Image: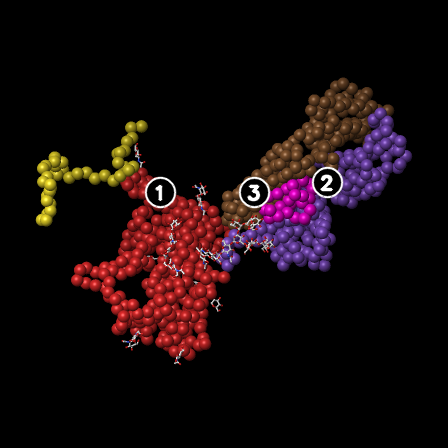
Chain colours: A brown, B purple, C red, D yellow
Amino acid sequence: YVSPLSVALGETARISCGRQALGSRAVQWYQHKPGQAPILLIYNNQDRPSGIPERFSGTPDINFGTTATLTISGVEVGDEADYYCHMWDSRSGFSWSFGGATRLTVLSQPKAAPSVTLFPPSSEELQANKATLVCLISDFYPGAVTVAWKADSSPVKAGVETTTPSKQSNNKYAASSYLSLTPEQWKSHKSYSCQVTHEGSTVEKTVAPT
Amino acid sequence: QVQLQESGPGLVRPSETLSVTCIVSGGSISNYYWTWIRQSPGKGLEWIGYISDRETTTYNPSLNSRAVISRDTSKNQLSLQLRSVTTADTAIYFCATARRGQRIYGVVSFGEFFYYYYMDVWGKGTAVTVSSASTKGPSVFPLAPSSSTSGGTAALGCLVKDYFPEPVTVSWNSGALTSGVHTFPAVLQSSGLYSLSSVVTVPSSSLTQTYICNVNHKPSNTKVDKKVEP
Amino acid sequence: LQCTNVTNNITDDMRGELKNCSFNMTTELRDKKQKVYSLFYRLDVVQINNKEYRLINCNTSAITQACPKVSFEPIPIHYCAPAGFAILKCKDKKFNGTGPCPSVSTVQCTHGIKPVVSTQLLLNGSLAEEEVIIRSENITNNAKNILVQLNTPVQINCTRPNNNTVKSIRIGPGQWFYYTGDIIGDIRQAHCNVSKATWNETLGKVVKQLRKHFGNNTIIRFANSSGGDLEVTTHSFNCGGEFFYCNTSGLFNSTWISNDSITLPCRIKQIINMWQRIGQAMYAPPIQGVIRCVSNITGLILTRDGTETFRPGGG
Amino acid sequence: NKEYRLINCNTSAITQACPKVSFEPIPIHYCAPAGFAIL
Ligand SMILES: *[C@@H]1O[C@H](CO)[C@@H](O[C@@H]2O[C@H](CO)[C@@H](O[C@@H]3O[C@H](CO[C@H]4O[C@H](CO[C@H]5O[C@H](CO)[C@@H](O)[C@H](O)[C@@H]5O[C@H]5O[C@H](CO)[C@@H](O)[C@H](O)[C@@H]5O)[C@@H](O)[C@H](O[C@H]5O[C@H](CO)[C@@H](O)[C@H](O)[C@@H]5O)[C@@H]4O)[C@@H](O)[C@H](O[C@H]4O[C@H](CO)[C@@H](O)[C@H](O)[C@@H]4O[C@H]4O[C@H](CO)[C@@H](O)[C@H](O)[C@@H]4O[C@H]4O[C@H](CO)[C@@H](O)[C@H](O)[C@@H]4O)[C@@H]3O)[C@H](O)[C@H]2NC(C)=O)[C@H](O)[C@H]1NC(C)=O
Ligand SMILES: *[C@@H]1O[C@H](CO)[C@@H](O[C@@H]2O[C@H](CO)[C@@H](O[C@@H]3O[C@H](CO)[C@@H](O)[C@H](O)[C@@H]3O)[C@H](O)[C@H]2NC(C)=O)[C@H](O)[C@H]1NC(C)=O
Ligand SMILES: *[C@@H]1O[C@H](CO)[C@@H](O[C@@H]2O[C@H](CO)[C@@H](O)[C@H](O)[C@H]2NC(C)=O)[C@H](O)[C@H]1NC(C)=O
Ligand SMILES: *[C@@H]1O[C@H](CO)[C@@H](O[C@@H]2O[C@H](CO)[C@@H](O)[C@H](O)[C@H]2NC(C)=O)[C@H](O)[C@H]1NC(C)=O
Ligand SMILES: *[C@@H]1O[C@H](CO)[C@@H](O[C@@H]2O[C@H](CO)[C@@H](O)[C@H](O)[C@H]2NC(C)=O)[C@H](O)[C@H]1NC(C)=O
Ligand SMILES: *[C@@H]1O[C@H](CO)[C@@H](O)[C@H](O)[C@H]1NC(C)=O
Ligand SMILES: *[C@@H]1O[C@H](CO)[C@@H](O)[C@H](O)[C@H]1NC(C)=O
Ligand SMILES: *[C@@H]1O[C@H](CO)[C@@H](O)[C@H](O)[C@H]1NC(C)=O
Ligand SMILES: *[C@@H]1O[C@H](CO)[C@@H](O)[C@H](O)[C@H]1NC(C)=O
Ligand SMILES: *[C@@H]1O[C@H](CO)[C@@H](O)[C@H](O)[C@H]1NC(C)=O
Ligand SMILES: *[C@@H]1O[C@H](CO)[C@@H](O)[C@H](O)[C@H]1NC(C)=O
Ligand SMILES: *[C@@H]1O[C@H](CO)[C@@H](O)[C@H](O)[C@H]1NC(C)=O
Ligand SMILES: *[C@@H]1O[C@H](CO)[C@@H](O)[C@H](O)[C@H]1NC(C)=O
Ligand SMILES: *[C@@H]1O[C@H](CO)[C@@H](O)[C@H](O)[C@H]1NC(C)=O
């Protein structure tokens, strides 16, 4: 499974590799973003492919006894991804499974107030005798928010479907919440308020039938 | 100098033959090694098998009883087939080119060396899901603006109602508009279907510019172009 | 013994060469026992038939280990005669080994002589002053071994790179056995090097003098040993404390007509029986660390077969 | 518990004396061979 690591922004990090070798090694260091194309940083302990910046480096085993640590100088927000450490040594055979995933985290990022937008059910969806209030949150950090629905003043607590926050291209987070209701209940209550609590701040968006 | 592009069905029934194809545009397929890797949710990524330039295959022992990899000569493509798939084979499949290096620590004559492999160039990746439920086409409903901030910047979007399975590709004006666009992760409703929404932030002075959202669901072969208007 | 391979994890070739063996053994108290494990070379154990094994010496002899303080490294020995007796040294540089010597001297003691027990290759011996000298009782008899003495020594580099460890285990009251504990680092093969060009040159100067008793035109060749016991068909010697047996097919593999370095794989023994009487066996206690010894090959023990072929040996 | 063991077991082998020899010391006169003397 995955093991966590926490590094400050701009400081150098040393990622430790598990299941260290018993003999001569030609290790591989792979960077994998969730769902994207994985990109290796190191194929031979020292060597890197063309295009990889000099910030990433791997420890050669110049004398037997050294461990494989992935050293990153000037850690930025884009370096936050999983890191796999493929291990090949003389004493062991064909290594099929990659090394344990290393969840790198870059602390001290600038927090962002959540950009919230509330959409009432569309006319064509109401034509289908269904309603889904859609509350979207974009461009916020850290990705830890709580969503609450309000009918006028009473909470809803029913028919709510919320996704875990997922990163976008802005290196901030994005999330969505769907409140499924019948058209009669949508027109029943005066207005509906989506409340997003981010850390100690709280943002409320209200929408009402025309 | 090599570009890889994965192509797969996205949905396969249980106990069948999953087939995916990786298209290569960079160079010849008989010069470098090639391999398949799969990323399953909740688990670390697994190395399943590889094919050499001399056309020799090797497979991971856990799935070697079920997997096979082939390489096309006329087409710059490499295919992967998996027999008798179950609910555990659902994953994002990546094709990758690989280079064979041998690491030597002693005398060449004695042996005392081993081959190590590394995958420098990868493909974008194709998602493959396994389920017995049939395919569903997405319903698209235009979420109109509220006429949202004080004035200038305002938000609109398109709601992709319940569908099956992932993913859904959403574009705007057939790719003409790119500023402020943001597509959000889908949600798995209790019905067993995914629903998403894609929004755009545009100035209120521009509001009509005839914004058309194009939704493509490959598993259902549905291309839906929907207009939005207040 | 209950024995397993040490899992090379590579192609299953030399897994038996070195083997992990667990067994029950006595302790300092008569009523209690202790179950322990060790590492045994392939050459010291034989199967039963499952993964059961047993020591080679059990069916044939009683076994005793050497005390770990005495060293098997040979040191010079000067042999001397008492009062009223003398040693006659012949100083002729072309002495055939038999017959009248014209220049004779007398001594009370010989020079420093190292008791090097070797086979097919004489190690750390004396050097011929000129040419290379060939000696045999009846050179025309193939049943008499041929002793070749060199004038230019050929250097040999022997090594076991396995970083072995010793494990002290109490067998009885006042008894501490020394097992092979573990192997630190890589598991490689013990082997010996000799420079190829020097060996070729010395083989040439050997055959030029061999032609003095068989003819200039007759073609002779060199091949490996023809068979017999282990100690005869191999280059057998004691390096660093442990007993090495090196395959010599890569040395005598040339046919010579009228007119970089090579390496030899070596295996390791520690259960050795005496070459005169079988019924007494010695266990060589394992030596810690990496073993490496450099020696001078200075002589050969060849055997004729009856063109001609020569095969080494001499047990 | 009340279990015990001999002191010599962990360190040495043990042998008992034969019960006929006496450890009582008796006089010893040390002497030199021919050609030597004691001062
Ligand atoms: C008795 O007789 C015996 C037989 O005659 C004799 O046996 C000899 O034993 C010794 C040891 O006991 C053996 O020595 C070993 O040699 C190994 C091989 O070294 C050769 O190969 C490497 C690698 O070659 C690749 O890379 C270069 C570029 O660097 C390319 O040009 C090559 O083409 C090749 O790359 C391609 O090909 C590969 C294979 O197809 C592909 O995989 C690859 O992708 C490419 O396509 C060369 O670099 C070596 O060159 C060096 O030596 C020459 C002379 O030959 C010198 O000019 C100069 O010094 C060169 O630097 C050589 O040609 C070694 O790997 C091995 O040493 C490693 O292992 C030990 C033990 O684990 C480590 O402690 C040690 O640190 C070494 O690790 C280094 O190297 C590896 C390999 O990359 C690294 O991964 C590792 O991190 C570390 O790198 C560090 O050091 C590098 C420099 O050394 C540096 O560049 C790095 O950046 C990093 O800092 C060991 O020395 C010897 O081979 C035996 N003899 C024979 C004939 O086999 C015995 O001695 C005799 N005597 C006795 C028993 O007493
Ligand atoms: C032929 O003679 C040579 C020397 O005359 C022998 O080489 C000697 O081998 C021994 C055992 O391998 C070496 O002893 C070791 O010395 C190192 C020194 O650092 C020490 O650390 C070890 O604990 C061990 O005592 C010895 O040094 C070495 N002599 C030289 C000059 O290097 C060789 O073994 C002889 N050949 C045969 C077959 O006996
Ligand atoms: C191996 O042979 C060489 C050459 O005969 C020996 O080197 C000689 O050693 C003697 C005695 O120590 C010296 O008097 C000579 O001057 C040395 N000559 C040279 C050229 O080095 C060497 O000692 C021999 N080694 C062994 C272990 O027998
Ligand atoms: C063989 O293994 C031993 C350990 O079993 C190694 O001994 C170490 O040597 C280094 C040398 O600086 C010391 O710092 C360590 O304290 C030693 N370890 C112990 C446990 O004593 C030895 O170096 C190895 N030899 C080879 C050739 O690999
Ligand atoms: C056996 O080992 C010795 C020493 O390890 C080798 O002799 C060395 O040769 C180099 C030549 O490059 C010299 O620079 C050193 O001074 C030599 N060492 C000594 C102690 O003289 C020798 O070449 C090896 N022989 C073989 C056949 O490999
Ligand atoms: C070691 O492996 C070899 C490989 O064929 C096998 O023949 C042998 O029985 C094995 N021995 C043990 C003790 O596992
Ligand atoms: C030691 O004796 C026990 C007796 O129960 C036996 O089970 C065990 O196999 C013996 N040890 C070995 C290595 O066979
Ligand atoms: C002891 O066993 C070995 C194993 O093959 C055999 O070669 C040898 O002849 C046996 N010795 C006796 C005396 O039975
Ligand atoms: C050795 O040389 C001497 C010198 O004449 C000779 O008499 C003798 O026959 C030779 N013996 C052999 C076996 O060559
Ligand atoms: C040497 O051997 C041959 C046959 O092998 C024999 O005829 C001859 O008599 C032997 N030489 C001596 C001196 O006995
Ligand atoms: C062999 O060659 C030598 C030259 O060193 C020569 O003196 C001798 O006469 C030759 N022998 C014969 C039989 O021709
Ligand atoms: C020695 O090596 C040769 C080839 O290198 C091989 O044919 C022969 O069988 C080997 N001898 C032994 C005893 O292993
Ligand atoms: C022995 O010589 C033959 C002929 O040159 C060669 O083919 C073979 O490889 C040699 N073997 C060894 C062990 O040197
Ligand atoms: C044996 O036991 C005694 C009891 O204290 C202890 O002093 C002594 O060191 C032990 N001997 C050994 C070799 O451990």
Give the Cα separation between the discs numbered 2 and 3. 38 Å
Residue pointed to by mark 2: B166
Q: Considering only vertical position in the picture, is B144 above or below C164?
A: above
Q: Which residues are magenta?
A: A32-58
Please name which of the two marks, 1 or 2, marks the residue nearer to the observer: 1
Residue pointed to by mark 3: A68
Residue C168 is labelled as 1
Does residue A92 show up? no
Residue furthest top as drawn: A153
Rendered residue at 63%/34% (across/down): A11
Q: Position of residue A129 (x, y in %)?
A: 81, 30
Q: Position of residue B93 (x, y in %)?
A: 67, 46
Rendered residue at 36%/52% (across/down): C241
Ligand 3 positioned in quadrant: bottom left
> Which one is nearer the viewer's eye here, D16 or A66?
A66
Q: Considering only vertical position in the picture, is C29 above or below C129?
A: above
> Which one is nearer the viewer's eye here, C171 or A58?
A58
Does residue D11 show up? yes
**Residue type highlighted by circle 2:** Glu
Q: Secondary structure at mark 3?
A: loop
